[PDB]
Length: 97
Image (tube, rainbow, N blue to C red; front, side):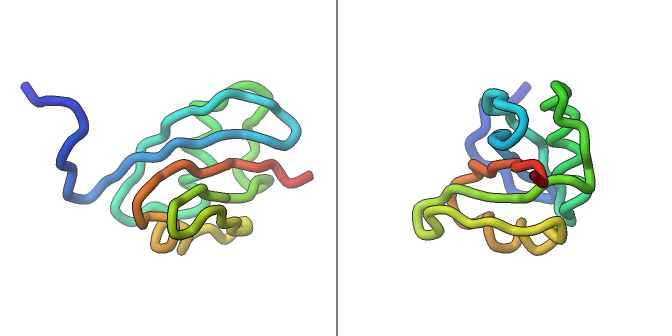
């Protein structure tokens, strides 16, 4: 039907979440929407990281990029998508500890 992720332009995106606080879990990819928000980020991330890491209102949204080496946004990571979406999508899901 279609090839691997090459040219994706519409009302969605991709994400690569990673937990590093109270639960040392491996990297996990999460789907992104056009109007994605903090609650959705942690929610979708928790679904993929369903290993003692299921707390929507208990995590922080960080990201590792080229121009933005490493950024960290609080629970209100609604604008996180408008900042982290520059090149890479390696975001860190840190629990509130």
